[PDB]
Image (cartoon, rainbow over all chains, first blue to last red):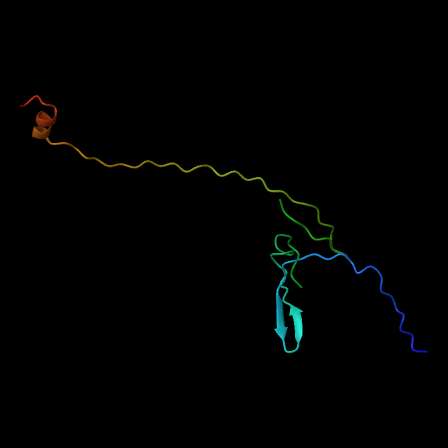
Length: 47
Length: 49
């Protein structure tokens, strides 16, 4: 019977974060290369 | 001090590592010479006037 309720609750708290956003076609997407960020000194390989 | 990533699986559990190293200052000395002329002494020191 057309169930539209779903859930919307807290409009959560947000923060301004330095990211990298590129527009490819009609979409906005994040360019993430995480090596220096996380894998850097850890000796775990970058997948 | 080095960061680590927490692995899941048959990966041996990693624990933090720390690095203490100590480099010794290299030493050196420099030179130059402006050596003075004989007559020039007997002028600037008075002594010849």
